Amino acid sequence: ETLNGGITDMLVELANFEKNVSQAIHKYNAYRKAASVIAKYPHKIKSGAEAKKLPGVGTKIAEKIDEFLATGKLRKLEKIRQDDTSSSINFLTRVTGIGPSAARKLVDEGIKTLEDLRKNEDKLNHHQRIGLKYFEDFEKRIPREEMLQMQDIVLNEVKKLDPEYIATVCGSFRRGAESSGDMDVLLTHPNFTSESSKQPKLLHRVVEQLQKVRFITDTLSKGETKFMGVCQLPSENEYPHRRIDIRLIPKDQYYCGVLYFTGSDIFNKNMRAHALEKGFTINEYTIRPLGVTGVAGEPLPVDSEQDIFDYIQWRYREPKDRSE
């Protein structure tokens, strides 16, 4: 239905821009009032020309009206899809090394595109570099065949080390996705408990090792609890590079830890609440009793995922079964 409808709509966004983007209460109000005006209006506006005759509808409008009435868009308007530098923010974000401010800066350097950065290697740091340098694979979703493949390796490898190590790959993959994005590996081992000292070498041993065997190509952040890095499959005739993060957790927290990293923000969200629901407070580290007034704690013993559920009384929603 509604004939003038197109023009009117166009008129709104155009108006909303000038108010929010700038200060001009005058331009907005205007663009604003024209809308008003044309809608009140009942005949299919054939051309802004005519339109001009109309009240509030000034010389300007018409043009913009007619331009729009012409090309199913407006040039002044078109700035929308571009957002200039702001598009770039999110673009840049895609890169691995870049974060909010970090990103903010490159663009304003003139570094909006990958292309810039391709030169400005320096303007970056080792993280930023890497990200770039392999960006592409970075966006090439993984496959379960692969996945399992890399999967096995890790879990296995660790074993070569000391079998009292617990590997677990989490993330989408666990839920049984057919396309995971990264390898979120959680790791642990009885020596390290929440009472334990900072145990770097643990997690470390293994990393270096993955690195040893050449499953690892670069280290994004060797830290003490966490390790971010890259891997890639073994060759013959090659498979891209994939992310991987080796997380190290205390054996007495590793569970919720798992449950959490297991899956779906929703389900977690759902889950977090239900406990709360039944008087339990839950987060990535523990399940604790929710006392009087909302504040209270003293986390219970956990040896397995069921242990959580049970507290918070739930039929086991298997991994697969967790998208909500």
Image (spheres, rainbow, N blue to C red):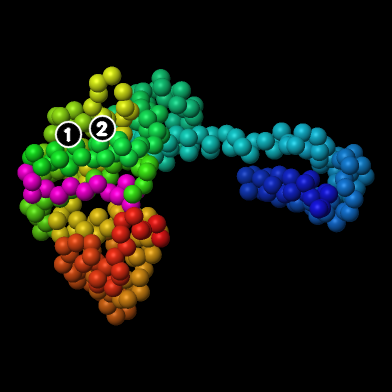
Q: Secondary structure at mark 2?
A: strand
Q: As drawn, is 88 to the left or to the right of 308?
A: right
- Given residues 141 and 8, the one toward you in this image is 141
Query: Mark 1 highlights which residue?
Result: 210
Task: Check the image and report above or below for 99 versus 320.
Answer: above
Q: How many marks?
A: 2
Q: Which residues are magenta?
A: 162-175
- Given residues 5 and 107, the one toward you in this image is 5
Mark carried by residue 231 = 2
Residue 138 in the image: state x and y as whole percent: 37, 33
Q: Main secondary structure of the magenta part?
A: loop
Which amino acid type is marked by label 2?
Cys
Residue 4 in the image: state x and y as whole percent: 83, 49
Residue 74 in the image: state x and y as whole percent: 73, 36
Which amino acid type is marked by label 1?
Leu
Task: Check the image and report above or below for 311 versus 250.
Answer: below
Mark carried by residue 159 = none
The image quadrant of residue 153 is top left
Q: As drawn, is 263 to the left or to the right of 56?
A: left
The image quadrant of residue 222 is top left
Residue lying at 62% horizontally and 44% vertically, measured from the top left: 21
Contact, CB < 8 Å: mark 1 with mark 2? Answer: yes
Residue 310 highlighted magenta (yes or no): no
Residue lying at 77% horizontally and 33% vertically, measured from the top left: 71
Which label's residue is closer to the chain start, 1 or 2? 1
